[PDB]
């Protein structure tokens, strides 16, 4: 069923979560990538990334306020993926597709990986 | 907006 | 704009936030309505409700783990609105529209209020 | 799904 649905709701929720992120409101984690720091909400990171879901469902790790990622991870690539988590928008460019696909494979973000391949398989 | 899902 | 967008992303994020809520994963607040308890995430409540946004941006209130709502609020009405926050789906019925519109006006949920009126203005 | 927003 009887339920009615508000089409822009899920996107409106995301818009607000990103405004809370930009204003540093109720952010509970710091992600460190090559000496650069990214403040986020653990639940948004879990909802998006299979890696972060594994990290925050771990009895010891769920308690950490700071998470250091693999040193190979480019901070720009991570920043472009953190923005996608919060906006549904991916700033995919020829200059960053390699760095962004490598960051999405690591974070277990299947849909980013999928399209990332398609753009290079068409570029070749 | 509201729609039938 | 150059950005590409994944259409189901925002809804997928919401689907996962609701699965975390159902499994009681990283829930940080307890909402009390007429002796009944609702476990949620403060950021989702803020993203949806103008009342909860005011509560969790308040220097003293943001620190509370338990929030008691006005006694007039029906727990079923609140439960139906908490489900809408997490799913974008509203279980609107003739038997609950009065209790659900009164709960949406209090929580400052304009879009629920708007449609709630429309259904009664057409019922009269 | 991917689209041009
Ligand atoms: N949150 C969350 C979550 C999940 N996050 C990883 C997303 C990349 C898929 C996967 C499965 N189930 C849950 Cl509850
Ligand atoms: N979160 C959040 C939020 C907000 N929540 C209330 C929603 C009902 C609208 C309103 C305005 N700005 C922000 Cl950051
Ligand atoms: Cl993804
Ligand atoms: Cl609303």
Image (tube, coloured by chain):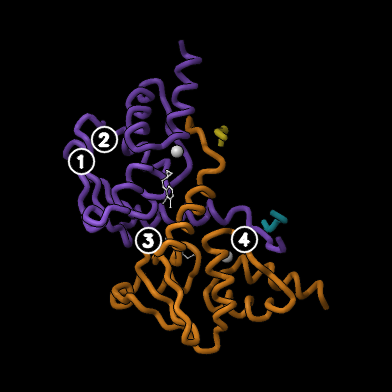
Chain colours: A orange, B yellow, C purple, D cyan
Identity of the residue drawn at 32% across and 53% down: C57
Identity of the residue drawn at 42% across and 33% down: C91
Residue that badge 3 annotates: A25
- Marks 1 and 2 in Cβ contact (< 8 Å): yes
- SS class, disc 2: helix
Q: Categorize mark 3 by other alpha carbons within 10 Å: few (<14), some (14-19), many (20+).
A: some
Q: Which mark is residue C36?
A: 1
- Marks 2 and 3 in Cβ contact (< 8 Å): no
Identity of the residue drawn at 50% across and 15% down: C122
Residue that badge 4 annotates: A89
The quarter of the rendered structure image containing the C terminus of chain A is bottom right
How far is disc 1 from disc 2 in space, using C-alphas?
7 Å
Q: Residue C75 carries which label?
A: 2
Is label 4 on the same chain as label 2?
no
How far is disc 4 from disc 2 in space, using C-alphas?
37 Å
> In the rendered view, does C94 fall on the left or right side of C29?
right
Label 2 CB less than 8 angstroms from ligand 4: no
Give the mark nearest the N terminus, 1 or 2.
1
Chain bearing tag 1 is: C
Q: In which quarter of the image is ligand 3?
A: bottom right
> In the rendered view, does A38 fall on the left or right side of A73?
left
Label 3 CB less than 8 angstroms from ligand 2: yes
In the rendered image, residue C121, in percent from the top left (x then y), is placed at 48, 16
């Amino acid at each position: 069923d009887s339920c009615i649905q508000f089409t822009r709701h899920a996107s409106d929720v995301l818009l607000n979560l990103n405004r809370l992120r930009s204003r540093d409101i109720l952010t509970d984690v710091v992600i460190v990538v090559s000496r650069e720091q990214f403040r986020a909400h653990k639940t948004v990171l879990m909802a998006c990334s299979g890696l972060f879901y594994s990290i925050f469902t771990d009895q010891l790790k769920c308690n950490l306020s700071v998470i250091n990622l693999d040193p190979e991870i480019n901070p720009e690539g991570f920043c472009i993926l953190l923005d996608f988590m919060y906006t549904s928008r991916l700033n995919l460019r020829e200059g960053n597709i390699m760095a962004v696909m490598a960051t999405a494979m690591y974070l277990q973000m299947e849909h980013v990986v999928d399209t990332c391949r398609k753009f290079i398989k068409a570029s070749e | 907006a509201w729609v039938i899902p």
